[PDB]
Each structure stands twice: as C-alpha cells, then as structure tokens.
Image (tube, rainbow, N blue to C red):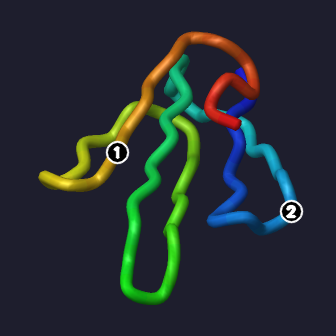
Amino acid sequence: LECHNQQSSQPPTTKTCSGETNCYKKWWSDHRGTIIERGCGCPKVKPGVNLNCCRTDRCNN
C-alpha cells in the first residue's frame, strides 16, 4: 500500500507503508500558511489539526 508523503502544496509524492495498511493526511492552518503532512499509517494529531485515514492506495493525497 502506498501513501502520499507530500507536504503542504509541495510536489505530490508517495511512500511504501511498512507494517501499515492505511494512509493518513494531516493539514492545518498557520500564520505562515497551511501546513500539510501526509504519510503511511494512521497516526494521531492534536486538536485543531486535521487528519484523514483511509485504506486506499494514494488515498491520502
């Protein structure tokens, strides 16, 4: 299973999930801009931050 590892508006990327079978996508706003952090797995984010987990390849794009 592949999950996007691209940050912010940066170039769309992907990475192989090891031991994981879900893709997560984190994104939030800041005084500097909207930060976006994606990767393999389904980690936990703090209050205010957005997170989306799915069981689809490059679903966390």
Task: Determine the residue positioned at 75% across, 44% down.
Answer: 15
Return the x and y of residue 37 as percentages of the image width and height. Answer: 52, 58
Task: Determine the residue positioned at 54% across, 60% down.
Answer: 36
Q: Amino acid at mark 1?
A: Asn
Return the x and y of residue 28 as percentages of the image width and height. Answer: 39, 59
Return the x and y of residue 52 as percentages of the image width and height. Answer: 43, 30
- Judged left or right of residue 11, residue 51 is left
- The CA span between labels 1 and 2 is 20 Å
Q: Which mark is residue 11?
A: 2
Q: Quadrant of the C terminus?
A: top right
Residue 13 versus residue 57 in the image, above or below: below
Residue furthest bottom in the image: 32
Circles 1, 2 touching at the beta carbon (< 8 Å): no
- Judged left or right of residue 60, residue 37 is left
Task: Determine the residue positioned at 55% across, 29% down.
Answer: 23
Return the x and y of residue 6 as percentages of the image width and height. Answer: 71, 57
Q: Quadrant of residue 14?
A: top right
Please state which of residues 16 and 11 is positioned toward the viewer in this rendering. Answer: 11
Q: Quadrant of residue 7?
A: bottom right
Mark 1 lies on residue:
50
